Structure formats: structure tokens, C-alpha cells
Figure (cartoon, rainbow over the protein chains, first blue to last red):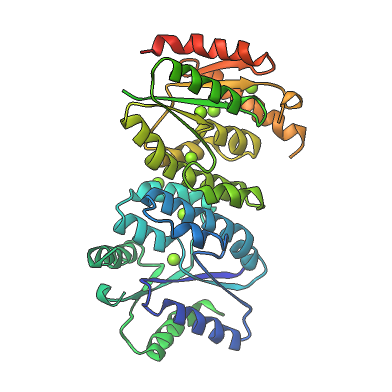
Length: 185
Length: 187
Ligand SMILES: [Mg+2]
Ligand SMILES: [Mg+2]
Ligand SMILES: [Mg+2]
Ligand SMILES: [Mg+2]
Ligand SMILES: [Mg+2]
Ligand SMILES: [Mg+2]
Ligand SMILES: [Mg+2]
């Protein structure tokens, strides 16, 4: 059956660190794990394309989406099918927060693109590492992005678990572990 | 006072040739013209990436869409705003033909994706260079037949936008026919 988990937040929020520690904890539990990330998990070359100077928000989202489509199809769905716990460091919510809340793109369009792109795959849980924006385009943009993530979590409070990114790393990892314990047996 | 025109059809249907001839004709009429193409008119690296890579149809489409988004914003709309006749060898109809009719992607989704990607920009006229895949001068034949039939299906639903030409005809006969259809829109 597998289990799909994501870690989200601004760059420098510790989401990469936590993804990694989660992968290792679950592994010690004897659970097969597949650790992945966006962007690049589908099309590693998308990382080049994404840095294009003055890229329109629409084009940026579409590149993220192309990578995501490939990632879901070639990496994530097959990992779940094999019974793995698949953990992604960034997924759809990142796009929604950066390209939607940050760059202003309409959420409904983002979600319609995403519906075929992802084959409707949602994570069972998403751990949001909430980081003050000054610790991450400029400050106004990162404020919109930070708040955007918080908006998405309010909106799907069953799937999101919001954690304070300024806590010590080992306390964050323990909180992730406690939200996860019920879903393992 | 811009005018957006596209050329569509299979690879080898004479698009480049006719684009070039139509640009010349407009130049002769004293009309500023800009000649462009997809893929790669937005993000050149999507074109080269996709020459050598084996993706899901959805990923392929979305990469073409990203290129198209940049193309429309950075090249097409700016040329139109300057009053140029902008001619693209390939546009959204190519993705619908190849990825929708060819690879089987849902057509409404493709259109909804394209709606923001293009800012709603549609060609005023699109010249479809129709020919059987076996006749093209530049999956197997079945895929290409689906694609060819896709273009013809798009055309028959949109007779106010498409002009269909038999692409097996001599190059100059095709050009004359394109010019006749175009004249009413000029100047
Ligand atoms: Mg997406
Ligand atoms: Mg996520
Ligand atoms: Mg929607
Ligand atoms: Mg067209
Ligand atoms: Mg498109
Ligand atoms: Mg047909
Ligand atoms: Mg159709």
C-alpha cells in the first residue's frame, strides 16, 4: 500500500534536514523508505530551466509541474506500489505557496494543472516547517510565501502538521515522529 | 495593429517553407513581420531537452506549455504590440494534435492548462498543411495518422480560424492559396 509523506516550507526551514532524519528513523523501524525531492525528482534538468532569468510565473509553475508529473509517475507511484514509505522534500504545496501566494497565480488554475500532473496523489501527511520569512525576490515575497503555506495548512488541517522551524532540530524530529507513530502499525 | 498567424501540420508538411514565403509576401506589402516557431521560441532548452529525452505525455505537454508561456509573453505579445504580423510555425494546435489526439491526453485539461499559459492568445488564422504521414517531405505510422486526423478534427470544428491546404501540392500553389485567404485581413 505504501505511505506518502511530504515536508514543506521555505528554503532554510530545515525541511530537508527533517526529511532526511525521518527517512532514517523509519528505516530503523524496518520500514522500506524512498527519499526524494522537488524540483528534480522527475526531470533533473528542470533545475536548469527554473533558473532562467525573468521567467514568467506561469512558465515557472509549468516547469515545476512537468517535473512533478514525471516524479509522480516514475518515482513516487512506483515506490508506493512496492510498499515503501515515500518521503518528498517539497511537493505540490510548495508550488501553491511560491507560485500562487508568492507570485500571484490563480490557485484554481494551479490545481487543475496539478490534477492530471499528479493523478490526484496527495500525501497522507505534510509536515510544514514554519520559518520566519527574514530567515529564508525580496522580503515581501517571502512573507507572502510563508503566510501562504500557513493558509494551505489551515485549509487542510487533517493533512498538515505545522511545526515551529525555530525549535531545535531534535525537538522537531520528535514531533514529526509522534504524529507519525499512529500511521505505522 | 498586430496580426497573429500560425502554420500547423505534421513535421514535413512544408510549414517552414510556407512560413518563409508568407513572411516574404508580407515584407513585399510593406508590413512588419516576425517569424517564430515552437518548440523553443520561449525556452530554447526545452527544445533541446526533448530532442533526447523519454518523458510521460503529461510531462512533455507541461514542458511544451512552459516554453509556450515564455514564447507568448516574451516574443509573440511584444511583436504584436509593436504592430507586427507574428507568424509561428506551430502553436497550441500542435500540442492538442500530438499530445491529445496522438498520445491520448484529455483535451479539456490540455485546453485549461493552455488558457493561462497563452493568456488566451489565439491565432486569427491558422493554415493547416494537411497531408498523409507517408507524404511528409521531412510511435509508427498509426500515431502519426492520429495526429494528422487530430489536426483535421480541430480544423473542422473551427472553420472561422483554420484554412486547410493540401500540403502535397506544389509549393507556389500553396503560397498563392495562403495569400488569397490572407488578403481580406490586409491592411
Ligand atoms: Mg503541479
Ligand atoms: Mg507537500
Ligand atoms: Mg481547480
Ligand atoms: Mg496554431
Ligand atoms: Mg499549452
Ligand atoms: Mg479527422
Ligand atoms: Mg478537439
